[PDB]
Image (cartoon, rainbow, N blue to C red):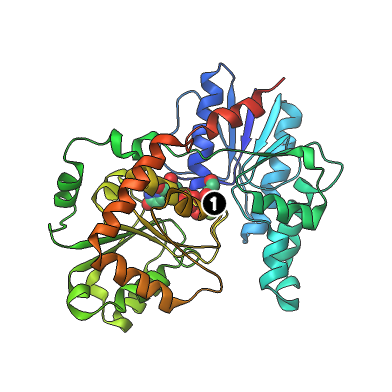
Amino acid sequence: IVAFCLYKYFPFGGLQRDFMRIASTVAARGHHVRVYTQSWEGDCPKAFELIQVPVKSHTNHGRNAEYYAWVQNHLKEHPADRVVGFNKMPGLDVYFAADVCYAEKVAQEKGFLYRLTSRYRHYAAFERATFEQGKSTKLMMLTDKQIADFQKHYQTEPERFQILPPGIYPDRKYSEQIPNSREIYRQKNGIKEQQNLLLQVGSDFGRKGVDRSIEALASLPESLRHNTLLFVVGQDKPRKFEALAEKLGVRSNVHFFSGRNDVSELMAAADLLLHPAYQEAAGIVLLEAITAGLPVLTTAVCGYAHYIADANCGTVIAEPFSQEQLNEVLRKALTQSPLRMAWAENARHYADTQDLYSLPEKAADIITGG
Ligand SMILES: O=c1ccn([C@@H]2O[C@H](COP(=O)(O)OP(=O)(O)O[C@H]3O[C@H](CO)[C@@H](O)[C@H](O)[C@H]3F)[C@@H](O)[C@H]2O)c(=O)[nH]1
């Protein structure tokens, strides 16, 4: 019996999609998969034993604490052979690092008033419980930067870390698309042959720099701008970003969508992925774009930004972030189709020659070992 703990399941998050693929891999090896969550949106594999954990606190942090306590009591009466968490909490045998190091985030960005909160104390305590010395929890990591951060704040025993290769779903790959996918999916989405489709995918618009993408769109020269659209796709509220698009006179150019299940089609249809995130532990969409043959503009803060430079299929905007640099890079990329075509080819080549896929098998090995 392998128990999985994540606070919330829904289809439009990387943490959730990585969990689904890892847990499905574990189940397919013959183990019984039990899932504890506060809430579950979308389909659930019939193999899974799904347990909804009742909570009543009025804050995320309070509910998380209640969840941990309830799960511990349930495990006391119904033992599992291994407990695997996708969120930081006590009691895990294995943790998957979908998040950044919270202690480092706070140290770098926050001050005294931020640290006064019960919210801070909780998240710090649950991270500490996972990473501190003396714990047995195996730590499945996405980036070397994550490891450096956790070592800095917790002096975690180095042997407990294991970096995983990426785990991009094969259905995003250019070679897994129907013939004429670009034309078909452009037509499906109302994109004209001559238009530029910019694509931004992710369920945290603010964190992922949707504002930066809108600013970049707005900065384009008049004629180019008139031929350019931006699709913003994810389970988040568009309100603030609609207001910004109106402010900048590009409201009609920007199309907002809730969570979509057709991201593979959108990447086949698009001309550039924009992902100028403020914070991103890794960024699965960056590598999805690589596998789709979709060139990428992103920021150096993203854990997976280096892959864009490695694949030579876009531009990584350096820190400190310059909006003017992103604006110029966008204008250049859009006006230089030969550059974009070369980037796309480079992306496809990298996707064909690099392991961007095996994460769930390697994570399942760690989970089921022994
Ligand atoms: O409307 C939508 C919106 C998204 N998706 C999919 O959800 C995934 C999003 O993962 P991504 O790593 O890009 O961002 P995020 O969800 O913030 O992931 C966290 O967890 C990730 C690790 O699990 C980590 O990479 C990241 O840094 C964390 F913030 C990616 O596979 C998208 O194609 C979708 O299908 N439809």
Instruction: From the top left corner, tell me how far across and down residue 73 is, in percent.
Output: 74, 36
Residue type, label 1: Ala
Residue 193 horizontal side relative to residue 201, left or right: left
Instruction: From the top left corner, tell me how far across and down residue 218 is, in percent.
Output: 30, 77
Q: Residue furthest right?
A: 134
Q: Quadrant of the N terminus?
A: top right
Q: In this rendering, is residue 297 above or below 166?
A: below
Instruction: From the top left corner, tell me how far across and down residue 173 is, in percent.
Output: 34, 38
Residue 171 horizontal side relative to residue 56, left or right: left
Mark 1 vs ligand 1: CB under 8 Å? Answer: yes
Is residue 329 visible in the rendered image? The answer is yes
How many marks are shown on the rendered structure?
Answer: 1
Looking at the rendered structure, the secondary structure element under dot 1 is loop
Instruction: From the top left corner, tell me how far across and down residue 206 is, in percent.
Output: 47, 68
Q: Residue furthest top?
A: 30
| Towards the viewer: 55 or 196 | 196
Q: Are there few (<14), some (14-19), or many (20+) residues within 10 Å of tag 1?
A: many
Is residue 261 visible in the rendered image? The answer is no
Q: Quadrant of the C terminus?
A: top right
Residue 197 occupies quadrant: bottom left
Find disc 1 in the rendering and name its residue.
282
Residue at the image point whose x is 75% and y is 46% from the top? 130
Residue at the image point whose x is 26% and y is 66% from the top? 334
Residue at the image point whose x is 36% and y is 76% from the top? 215
| Towards the viewer: 140 or 116 | 140
Q: In this rendering, is residue 179 above or below 78?
A: below
Residue at the image point whose x is 33% and y is 69% from the top? 330
Q: In this rendering, is residue 278 above or below 281?
A: below
Residue 199 horizontal side relative to residue 80, left or right: left
